[PDB]
Image (cartoon, rainbow, N blue to C red; front, side):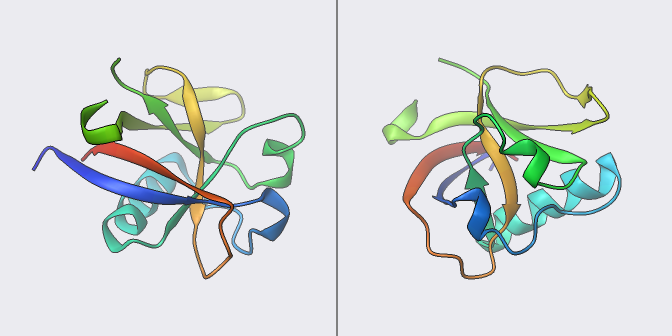
Length: 113
């Protein structure tokens, strides 16, 4: 399927144990997609002071359209040293590995895969 319904655990930035997906734009997009498939991906909501506490390159989920079955359609955009790879809508948050951190909420998304 071109899209997959996922329910992403929303993590507090100070709880996150693994603060990015890797060392290159291509690796972080690769690893993010793998962790989304495997159900091992968390979401951090972006506010003042969040991104400096996480590791670049960043992987964002961005709204791709204006929401089937309560799932916002999203796609992946990476960022490194102020340059983004991809073009999409509003950021819903930054993706990180999930390794058992307790979430505060869930974000239902329809991921363009």
